[PDB]
Length: 72
Length: 72
Image (cartoon, rainbow over all chains, first blue to last red; front, side):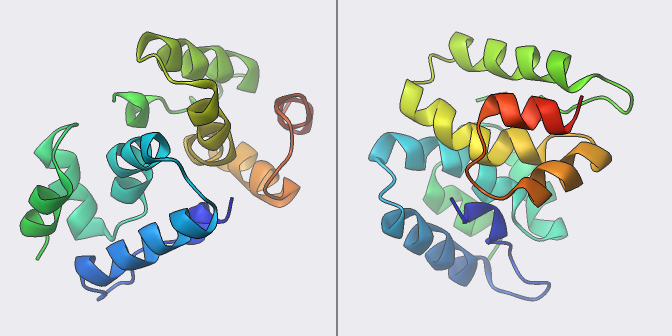
Protein backbone atom coordinates (compact mmCIF):
# COMPACT_ATOMS: atom_id res chain seq x y z
CA UNK A 1 0.00 0.00 0.00
CA UNK A 2 1.93 3.00 -1.39
CA UNK A 3 -1.03 5.35 -1.12
CA UNK A 4 0.58 7.24 1.78
CA UNK A 5 3.05 8.57 -0.80
CA UNK A 6 0.43 10.28 -2.94
CA UNK A 7 0.51 13.93 -1.83
CA UNK A 8 -0.85 16.94 -3.69
CA UNK A 9 1.92 19.20 -4.99
CA UNK A 10 2.40 22.77 -3.65
CA UNK A 11 0.92 24.20 -6.88
CA UNK A 12 -0.60 20.99 -8.29
CA UNK A 13 -4.24 21.29 -9.52
CA UNK A 14 -6.64 19.19 -7.38
CA UNK A 15 -7.82 17.50 -10.57
CA UNK A 16 -4.38 16.00 -11.29
CA UNK A 17 -3.89 15.04 -7.66
CA UNK A 18 -7.16 13.07 -7.95
CA UNK A 19 -6.08 11.11 -11.06
CA UNK A 20 -2.87 10.14 -9.27
CA UNK A 21 -4.82 9.04 -6.20
CA UNK A 22 -7.34 6.76 -7.90
CA UNK A 23 -4.81 5.58 -10.44
CA UNK A 24 -2.88 4.15 -7.47
CA UNK A 25 -6.00 2.63 -5.90
CA UNK A 26 -6.75 0.62 -9.09
CA UNK A 27 -3.23 -0.81 -9.26
CA UNK A 28 -3.64 -1.98 -5.69
CA UNK A 29 -7.13 -3.23 -6.62
CA UNK A 30 -9.04 -1.27 -4.01
CA UNK A 31 -12.67 -2.38 -3.87
CA UNK A 32 -15.36 0.28 -4.37
CA UNK A 33 -15.93 0.17 -0.61
CA UNK A 34 -12.29 1.05 0.11
CA UNK A 35 -12.31 3.91 -2.38
CA UNK A 36 -15.22 5.50 -0.48
CA UNK A 37 -13.32 5.46 2.80
CA UNK A 38 -10.13 6.68 1.17
CA UNK A 39 -12.02 9.58 -0.39
CA UNK A 40 -13.45 10.65 2.99
CA UNK A 41 -10.03 10.39 4.60
CA UNK A 42 -6.68 10.01 2.76
CA UNK A 43 -7.71 12.07 -0.30
CA UNK A 44 -8.50 14.92 2.07
CA UNK A 45 -5.40 14.44 4.22
CA UNK A 46 -2.82 14.08 1.42
CA UNK A 47 -4.00 17.35 -0.21
CA UNK A 48 -2.09 20.64 -0.17
CA UNK A 49 -2.60 23.05 2.80
CA UNK A 50 -5.17 25.35 1.21
CA UNK A 51 -7.24 22.54 -0.25
CA UNK A 52 -7.07 20.43 2.94
CA UNK A 53 -8.59 23.34 4.88
CA UNK A 54 -11.34 23.77 2.29
CA UNK A 55 -12.07 20.02 2.15
CA UNK A 56 -11.92 19.80 5.96
CA UNK A 57 -14.35 22.74 5.93
CA UNK A 58 -16.78 20.91 3.58
CA UNK A 59 -17.67 18.37 6.26
CA UNK A 60 -17.41 14.56 6.14
CA UNK A 61 -19.57 13.25 3.31
CA UNK A 62 -19.18 15.54 0.33
CA UNK A 63 -19.07 13.94 -3.10
CA UNK A 64 -16.01 13.92 -5.31
CA UNK A 65 -17.52 16.53 -7.65
CA UNK A 66 -18.15 18.88 -4.71
CA UNK A 67 -14.55 18.49 -3.52
CA UNK A 68 -13.18 19.33 -6.99
CA UNK A 69 -15.43 22.37 -7.13
CA UNK A 70 -14.32 23.67 -3.72
CA UNK A 71 -10.62 23.43 -4.76
CA UNK A 72 -10.60 24.33 -8.43
CA UNK B 1 -16.51 9.12 8.72
CA UNK B 2 -14.97 10.80 11.79
CA UNK B 3 -11.77 8.76 11.62
CA UNK B 4 -9.75 11.78 10.48
CA UNK B 5 -10.24 13.13 14.01
CA UNK B 6 -8.50 10.23 15.73
CA UNK B 7 -4.95 11.47 16.37
CA UNK B 8 -2.41 10.06 18.80
CA UNK B 9 -1.78 12.39 21.74
CA UNK B 10 1.64 14.07 22.28
CA UNK B 11 2.39 11.67 25.15
CA UNK B 12 -0.37 9.10 24.51
CA UNK B 13 0.76 5.42 24.52
CA UNK B 14 0.42 3.80 21.06
CA UNK B 15 -1.68 1.07 22.67
CA UNK B 16 -4.42 3.52 23.72
CA UNK B 17 -4.29 5.31 20.39
CA UNK B 18 -4.99 1.92 18.77
CA UNK B 19 -8.08 1.17 20.90
CA UNK B 20 -9.48 4.59 19.99
CA UNK B 21 -8.81 3.96 16.30
CA UNK B 22 -10.50 0.57 15.97
CA UNK B 23 -13.21 1.49 18.43
CA UNK B 24 -14.21 4.19 15.92
CA UNK B 25 -13.98 1.81 12.95
CA UNK B 26 -16.50 -0.60 14.56
CA UNK B 27 -19.03 2.15 15.20
CA UNK B 28 -18.80 3.09 11.55
CA UNK B 29 -18.99 -0.63 10.70
CA UNK B 30 -15.78 -0.83 8.72
CA UNK B 31 -15.46 -4.19 6.98
CA UNK B 32 -12.34 -6.27 7.69
CA UNK B 33 -11.05 -5.19 4.28
CA UNK B 34 -11.31 -1.50 5.19
CA UNK B 35 -9.56 -2.02 8.51
CA UNK B 36 -6.54 -3.48 6.67
CA UNK B 37 -6.20 -0.41 4.47
CA UNK B 38 -6.74 1.95 7.38
CA UNK B 39 -4.01 0.18 9.34
CA UNK B 40 -1.51 0.56 6.48
CA UNK B 41 -2.41 4.21 6.08
CA UNK B 42 -4.49 6.32 8.54
CA UNK B 43 -3.27 4.50 11.68
CA UNK B 44 0.26 5.36 10.64
CA UNK B 45 -0.55 8.92 9.60
CA UNK B 46 -2.64 9.94 12.62
CA UNK B 47 0.14 8.83 15.03
CA UNK B 48 2.41 11.18 17.00
CA UNK B 49 5.65 12.45 15.35
CA UNK B 50 8.06 9.94 16.87
CA UNK B 51 5.84 6.95 16.25
CA UNK B 52 4.91 8.06 12.70
CA UNK B 53 8.62 8.10 11.82
CA UNK B 54 9.13 4.65 13.33
CA UNK B 55 6.03 3.22 11.62
CA UNK B 56 6.99 4.94 8.34
CA UNK B 57 10.41 3.35 8.86
CA UNK B 58 8.90 -0.16 9.30
CA UNK B 59 7.80 -0.29 5.66
CA UNK B 60 4.31 -0.85 4.23
CA UNK B 61 3.00 -4.22 5.39
CA UNK B 62 3.95 -4.70 9.01
CA UNK B 63 1.42 -6.37 11.27
CA UNK B 64 -0.36 -4.61 14.10
CA UNK B 65 1.73 -6.44 16.72
CA UNK B 66 4.95 -5.29 15.02
CA UNK B 67 3.74 -1.68 14.99
CA UNK B 68 2.92 -1.79 18.72
CA UNK B 69 6.34 -3.25 19.43
CA UNK B 70 8.18 -0.56 17.44
CA UNK B 71 6.36 2.22 19.38
CA UNK B 72 5.99 0.84 22.88
